[PDB]
Amino acid sequence: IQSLKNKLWDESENPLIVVMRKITNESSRVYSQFKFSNESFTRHLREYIVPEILEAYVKGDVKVLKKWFSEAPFNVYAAQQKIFKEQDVYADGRILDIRGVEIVSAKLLAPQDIPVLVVGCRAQEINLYRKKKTGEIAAGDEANILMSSYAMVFTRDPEGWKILEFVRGGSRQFT
Amino acid sequence: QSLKNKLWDESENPLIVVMRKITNESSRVYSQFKFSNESFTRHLREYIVPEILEAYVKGDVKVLKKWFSEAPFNVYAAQQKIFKEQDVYADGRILDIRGVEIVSAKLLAPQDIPVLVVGCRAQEINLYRKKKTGEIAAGDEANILMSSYAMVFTRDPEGWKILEFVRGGSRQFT
Ligand SMILES: [Cl-]
Ligand SMILES: [Cl-]
Image (tube, rainbow over all chains, first blue to last red; front, side):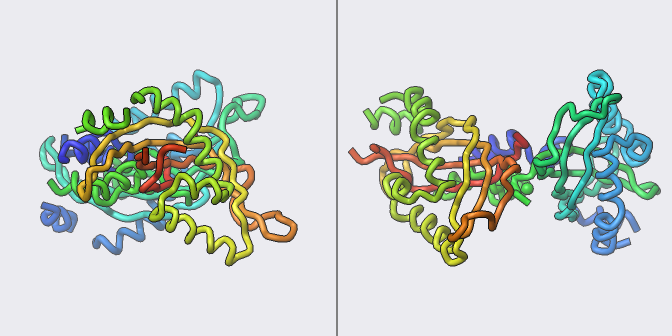
């Protein structure tokens, strides 16, 4: 049934189609726009950009993410920080391994015609928070290893790129 | 268009994986077991699911021989053989069992069999030990894994059987 695919589409919490919903709700003119090569900048994402953004996103680093993140996604990140400020607790987490770092989609959207690159990856990390003064764990485990999933909407300037939309999720992969 | 079919084709969500093979009305399936829907859903979370998953992680085959039919037990026995080929045994433990619900009821295409699809999520630790001095081979004792289960039910007049079974892969961290 077509209804089952439709239900699965707008009900799944995989970062990639979460992102895909808010771009839509062909790829030929996208790759010619930037000129650089897809394959040459795929490993350049995996080399520097992705690890540098992830460890920043995990530790709670705002000054670096303010650069990469656009006006709206950074706002929704800073708003997530309020609660941690309110609970008087700080982010103490790190990223162990980042495997799965490739460019899936390439599309342009409704407001004007901004070209966009969609980057998906899986990461391995622990997520814990310590009390601002006692340095004691408030929430989160080290013993527990977390398998996260990511979807980044990239754009270019006509340091380097900008994140148009970002989402942390959970990978079904055990490693 | 492209994007909606591609997901349905390439998703490893146990639920739609099971549902992808089936697709090759509910009211005709339910009143055929007479029994009721909600009395089965609570009987799953309190008898069947705990009883079947208990055996799955521990490897207990004398239980899964009763519930599993020939095709998915073939899939399970073959997986288990490789554990033995490594002198390893399944010392797993399911800690929590939360997500328990019959998501769909369908009649298969080959013949008119009444089928009920049960969606599931569970907290568990995966661990393996050697034969002599059963200690460690695989997994971590203090690492909680979230697993997504899916299963297809029917009965032959401890009552039910399982024709299809797939496991593993929750997006939930807890
Ligand atoms: Cl995944
Ligand atoms: Cl999914």
